[PDB]
Image (spheres, coloured by chain):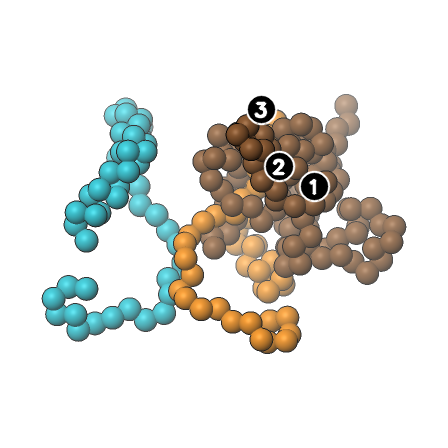
Chain colours: A orange, B cyan, C brown
Amino acid sequence: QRKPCDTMKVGGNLDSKGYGIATPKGSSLGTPVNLAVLKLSEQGVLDKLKNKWW
Amino acid sequence: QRKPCDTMKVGGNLDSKGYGIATPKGSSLGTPVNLAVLKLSEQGVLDKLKNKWW
Amino acid sequence: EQKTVVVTTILESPYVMMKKNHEMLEGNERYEGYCVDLAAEIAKHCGFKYKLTIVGDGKYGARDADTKIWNGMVGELVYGKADIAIAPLTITLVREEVIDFSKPFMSL
């Protein structure tokens, strides 16, 4: 979408993969942010972010 | 790809999801099953069976 | 009593964007974007205090050869420059064995 519109996709994409937050081993912060991500994942607020940023 | 060959896909995949083997809540064999799944995955048998059948 | 943490993120233009007043702002004000307002929402639920920082290597970066010792962005966690990562980064076991990951937020 960032003009010039001189680039295009071809092919039906290659694979399926996830993006997520990460945290080093033993860090106490991990699960208390993971539950917040789970909240957002089930509340769907991410759709607002996707709209805003694409 | 089956004999009639009279139908076809259109477009790409709409999303992504995955399969897992399932059992009732807390089924004690479930963790042995998870180990079996992990070993058959590491052994590449998930290709072997698919490579036979498709 | 009080506690604070340092966060790693990256200037991929869909995910983080440099606000025009880029001369002198702090990372908690320098930036906007999908990672930035996701992080803000997460901090809104979890309440912890933090500061955003760019990955100091500024890149994904490779494994160290034969050692597989980390690139900048993972080493900054394991070696304490930061304590959490909120970035477009692919989940894989070759990373999961070393550090924990959230539930994925997107599938792509």
Q: Residue C57 carries which label?
A: 1
Q: Residue C29 carries which label?
A: none
Give coordinates of residue A30: x percent, y percent: 58, 32
Disc nearer the start of the sequence (2/1):
1
Could you give the CA–CA distance between mark 2 and mark 3, rounded to whole angstroms? 20 Å
> In the rendered image, which residue does mark 2 sit on?
C71
Helix, strand or loop at label 1? It is loop
Look at 71% across and 57% down and name the residue there.
C17
Q: Mark 3 lies on which chain?
A: A
Look at 48% across and 30% down and name the residue there.
C97
Could you give the CA–CA distance between mark 1 and mark 3, rounded to whole angstroms? 24 Å
Q: Which chain carries label 1?
A: C
In the picture shown, does residue A25 fall above or below C71? above
Callout 2 crowding tier (Cα within 10 Å): few <14, some 14–19, many ≥20: some
Q: Viewed as shown, does residue C97 lie left or right of C13?
A: left
Callout 1 crowding tier (Cα within 10 Å): few <14, some 14–19, many ≥20: few
Q: Which mark is residue A26?
A: 3
Tag 2–tag 1 contact (CB < 8 Å): yes
